Length: 50
Length: 50
Image 1 (tube, rainbow over the protein chains, first blue to last red):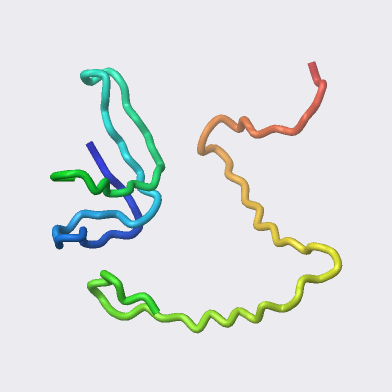
Image 2 (image 1 turned 45 degrees about the horizontal axis):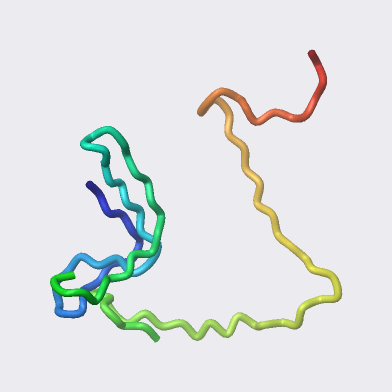
């Protein structure tokens, strides 16, 4: 599973690995029977442990 | 100015970009480019050859 994007930076607490724009997501799905290609903006949810 | 999470520097622009007033008619730029042999040459003009 991959996460490709142009710009990268720290999260709120400080852990690396956040992409700040449209991000390409290559997520295999369907118990290895389907590949998702998403070009979306990913917003960190404020919920617990998110 | 940005310098947000660059991890390599500051990142400024005085993007004055002279905002020259819009002309009476809209004017546009076009950069065309074609490729051969990288696929089937499938981008073809409209015809009724038969």
